[PDB]
Image (cartoon, rainbow, N blue to C red; front, side, top):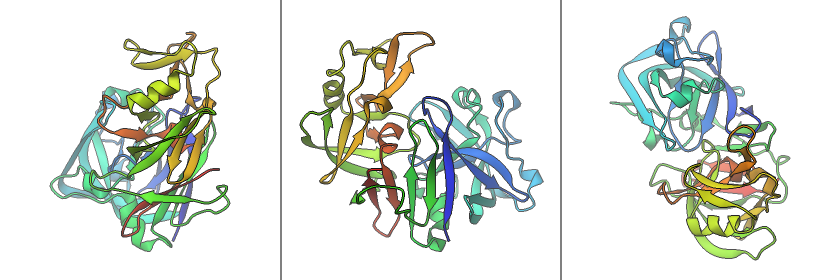
Length: 330
């Protein structure tokens, strides 16, 4: 089997992407944030505290003839941005782009933190990291990809995120029309539960490539590119007036600037992030200070190849017995 679904930016900055997902019988379609940095499929629901729901579409398990309470199971997750959610668990039929999994754990939120409530466009998350990170207790549950894998034509999914435009998540096949050149594959460590790999270096604009190992994670659920402070300083030093602002929370730059590109290495191959992809717009409405799309990872503990980086590539998440990542230009 295969599946193919369009993913759409939630706003004009590409702060996140939403993909429609069918849950239950008859189908209830929710727009989920596909997150290769986590491993829980959780949704706003009829069980979510009413004051914490503000415009989201909810899953109502009592209206699904295929929903079953997973008795005794609870979940609770906290994300790198400080947001969180928790609740109980049903199993139900879940379909993405024509690919159907029966018996998928659907984690129903009883509580969500303010940032989820405040984002009316995201109805939940669909985790695509390794199932070892799934938070369901006392019986850990599998991701949608893990459940689908054996049925897929090939044990892979691909992320093709658009810049200020829709893109595609495919399951079970590699669309050879969706990229240019060849796909360069690189090793993955699953030891932390992430799609963790090592970039071979970087360049800023037309500058020379610096060969240096940068361990980090391919994370579709993180907006920006978070890299070591040395790398980030070298980038922003090429932008007149750019500076790190403790009050804003990262590098800012004059909105009048034209940003240089940023290149990252995948083996001997190179992925070029155009400068425009690094502009996240005014820090507050009407400001002439703009927020940068490349930020330091120094306070995180891990480097994160988030959407800023991934949207410059066609990315293969290869879930073969030994997982790997592939990157192609597009």
